[PDB]
Structure formats: structure tokens, C-alpha cells
Length: 122
Length: 122
Ligand SMILES: O=C(Cn1ccc2c(=O)[nH]c(N3CCC(Cc4ccccc4)CC3)nc21)Nc1ccncc1Cl
Ligand SMILES: O=C(Cn1ccc2c(=O)[nH]c(N3CCC(Cc4ccccc4)CC3)nc21)Nc1ccncc1Cl
Image 1 (tube, chains in turn blue, yellow):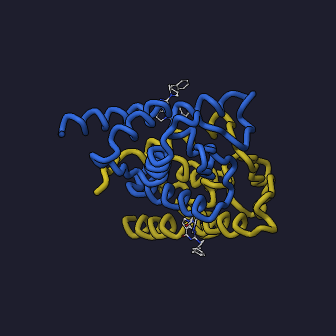
Image 2 (image 1 turned 135 degrees about the vertical axis):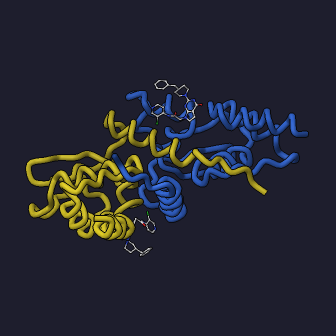
């Protein structure tokens, strides 16, 4: 009973990543050792179980700075952060493990599973 | 060189609409005559030329209340607001005009064009 716009969701995600590229309405900085990454809490909740659980919590929802455990690999987080904003996963042999272990910490179950299927295909 | 996750963008949009259904991280109320609608500015910028232009403007970006012209049809705005959050357009013969004229006011060019193709198919 309703017309489906099959590329609207990808169009929207492209525009959210535009806004993040320009720092418009970003509302948190993620400290990953020496790196910082600004983002929209909503987009992070929408992609990670770690961030969903942190920010649904009234006690932590209005945080503007999140410090990840300094054991997180910054490249792995950047590749996953970009995945969140583009729906594209840069998996190389060269960083599969770092990405997997970072996607587990971030409670990104489907991405972790894709990494398991990635291993097999090696 | 990158694995494409073909439903990630739709999954994300579903979660943003969950958050809107629960009022998590909503940051504006849209007054349309007697109706109010809470939403995420980012999602509205990502879908409407009116809201993009209002909120990219540093002078208006931190508005928490937008009052639309009381000539806007509230049903038409609700159908378009829901489209923004689901990628589904409820076009009926019964409200095509109201939706079209509301999508023009909101600078939603593709939706307006779909309404023109909708007319033809009548
Ligand atoms: O789904 C995401 C974000 N995302 C994406 C993948 C993924 C993942 O693999 N795991 C989780 N978890 C957090 C909540 C989970 C189940 C749950 C659902 C509802 C209430 C309690 C628990 C378990 C772990 N989140 C994930 N966000 C989201 C979820 C629900 N409603 C709105 C949004 Cl925005
Ligand atoms: O595209 C949307 C939101 N959206 C969705 C459809 C649609 C539409 O049909 N028209 C406009 N207009 C606003 C800006 C337009 C061109 C422009 C682009 C860049 C700079 C100046 C002008 C003309 C009218 N927006 C639209 N948002 C968005 C756009 C760009 N970057 C980030 C985001 Cl979030």
C-alpha cells in the first residue's frame, strides 16, 4: 500500500556522513589513544551494541567524550566507524584480526560474523 | 576492495526510527498547527532541503523548536516525516495533492517527482 524508495536509506547515510565530514551536529568525540573521532551518537547507537548500551543509559547519554580502552586498535576503530557511515567494510588480510577484535569490543555482531566468513575464505 | 553490506543503510534507518519512537536523542520539535512532532535534526537535514538549509545555518542550527507555516497540512507532513524514517511513501489518491504540495514546501525533490509520476499513473 506504500511506495518503497529503494535507495533512500543509502542516500540518507551518505548525507549523515557529509554532516560528519563537516562536523555539523556531531555530539561526541571518541578518544582512541592518541586519536580523536567526532560522530553522531545516534549513528553510533544505530550500529554498535557498546554505544547503544552506553547512550540509552540516562546516566551516560549526555556524555560528550567517550574514552575507549587504550588497548583498542585505532585503525580498526576507524575502519569500523567508516563502515558505520558508508556500509562498506575494508577487510584486508593485513588487518582482519585487528578489525575482528575491535568489532567484538564494539558489539557489532554481523561485522564480526563477516570476519569469521572472511577467515574461512582464507 | 571493500565488502558492501547491502542492508546496513536500511538497518541503520530502522534504528534511528526506533530512537525517534522512544524519544532518544531527539533534538527538535516541529510545530505543525495543533500537532507536534519530535525528530533528529540530522535525519531531517538528510531528507529535506528546507531543514538542511535551516540547520546548516549557524544562526538557526541550535533551534529546538521549528514552527511550520500554519498552511502546511499536518497529515502530509506526518506521511513525509515517516517516509524520512522508513523510506516508504503512503501515496493514496485521497491525499496525493496534500502530500505533493507538502513535499514541495519541504524541498524533497525526488518525492515531488514521484508524486508527478503518481498523477500520470492516474
Ligand atoms: O541495534 C543497534 C545497533 N547495533 C547494530 C548491531 C548491533 C549488535 O549486534 N548488538 C547490539 N546490542 C545492543 C542491543 C542489543 C539487543 C537489544 C535491543 C533493544 C533493547 C535491548 C537490547 C544487544 C547488543 N546493537 C547493535 N541499536 C539499537 C537497538 C535497539 N533499538 C534501537 C537501536 Cl538504535
Ligand atoms: O540532500 C540533503 C537533504 N535532501 C534530500 C533531498 C533534498 C533536495 O531535493 N534538495 C535539497 N536542498 C538542500 C541543498 C541542496 C543542494 C546543496 C548541497 C550542498 C550544499 C548546498 C546546496 C539544494 C536544496 N536537500 C535534500 N541534505 C544534504 C545536502 C548536502 N550535504 C549534506 C546534507 Cl545532509
